[PDB]
Image (tube, rainbow, N blue to C red):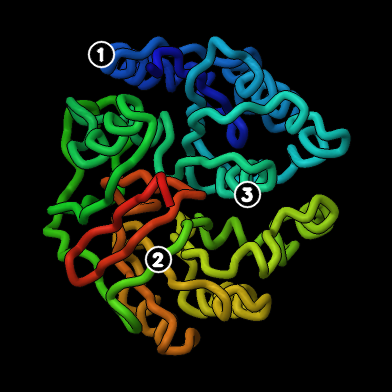
Amino acid sequence: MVSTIGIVSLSSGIIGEDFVKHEVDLGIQRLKDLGLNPIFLPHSLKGLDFIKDHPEARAEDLIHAFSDDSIDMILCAIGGDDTYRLLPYLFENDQLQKVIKQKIFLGFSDTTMNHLMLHKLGIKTFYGQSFLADICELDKEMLAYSLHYFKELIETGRISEIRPSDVWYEERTDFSPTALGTPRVSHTNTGFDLLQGSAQFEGKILGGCLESLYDIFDNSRYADSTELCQKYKLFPDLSDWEGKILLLETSEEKPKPEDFKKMLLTLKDTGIFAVINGLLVGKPMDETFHDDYKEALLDIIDSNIPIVYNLNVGHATPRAIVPFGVHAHVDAQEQVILFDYNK
């Protein structure tokens, strides 16, 4: 019985900018048609500059979203690259833990950091879509495959299974008003690609955007990312990772193959690939460096660890939604991932 959906800006504040107005109205109408009543949290529409300079305000919006019993679901507006800055405002005095309640939380990319924050507090979240990226798809309707998962989530509170899309789409090259009502360029999608290891494996899924996870360990983007993430122990320990399935997906930054490898090896050094039950990897945006990443994965990760590539999760389109913290059964041969809420 999800009815009210609260939209939050925890990363970029672009959603409140004048030029995005029509897109926002488009998404609002789509949410209404699905049986929902959208509300924007108090700071979420204040714009680029305000949101950038007030991570504490973003945190206050998140705290309110989780503590307000009239809000049934929380949807991230859009990603960015600096939501790690919210950490002290959520954890230094257990501000979020004190008032948090289990309810649907959906986002991706920079939101990976928020997913890890919520994991720390025992909250089961949902990865892979956001308001501007998916609900405000510029074509006449939302992408059918993306809609399938969003509709299922809002109607049932869960995702039961993921199957590959029939098609995938390129990122647009026109973002002016002439883009409205036009389709993205599409291509046939060939399904889950078992790179190595068992076609079947199981466990709860956790992870997200590779570039985001990298900033837990490397401070090149922001000098204090590693300090803050270590201070608040954001990265799960090995006992936590053991027997889980890791999700990785690459962003619009399209990391060059050398950098993709660097990032994988930084994770490998933690022991994560040694304790997980398998690895799921999303299709890169535009399939950029698709074959290079496949070769890098095969080279770096021991061949007894299962890896399934080409998931329609992450920055390519369309986009499935992945429950985190829910036992999953992967079967690459049968092109399906099942979720068991009673295991």
Q: Residue at x 67, y 67 (%)?
A: 239
Which residue position holds label 2?
202
> At label 2, which amino acid type do we have?
Glu
Which label sits in the foreground, 1 or 2?
2
Q: Is residue 278 above or below residue 15?
A: below
Q: Residue at x 45, y 49 (%)?
A: 326
Q: CA distance from mark 2 to mark 3?
A: 20 Å
Q: Is residue 243 above or below residue 232?
A: below
The answer to which quarter of the image holds residue 278 is bottom left
Q: Are marks 3 and 1 in contact (CB under 8 Å)?
A: no
- The residue tagged with tag 3: helix, strand or loop? helix
- The residue tagged with tag 2: helix, strand or loop? strand
Q: CA distance from mark 1 to mark 2?
A: 36 Å
**Circle 3 Cα neighbour tier, 10 Å, few/some/many (<14 / 14–19 / ≥20):** many
Task: Give left or right: position of 32 versus 112.
Answer: left
Which residue position holds label 3?
116
Quarter of the rendering occupied by the N terminus: top left
> At label 1, which amino acid type do we have?
Asp
- For the residue pair 299 and 339, the one nearer the viewer reads as 339
Which label sits in the foreground, 2 or 3?
2
Residue 33 badge: 1
Q: Are marks 1 and 2 in contact (CB under 8 Å)?
A: no
Q: Earlier in the sequence, mark 2 or mark 3?
A: 3
Residue 143 at least partly seen: yes
**Circle 1 Cα neighbour tier, 10 Å, few/some/many (<14 / 14–19 / ≥20):** few
> At label 3, which amino acid type do we have?
Leu
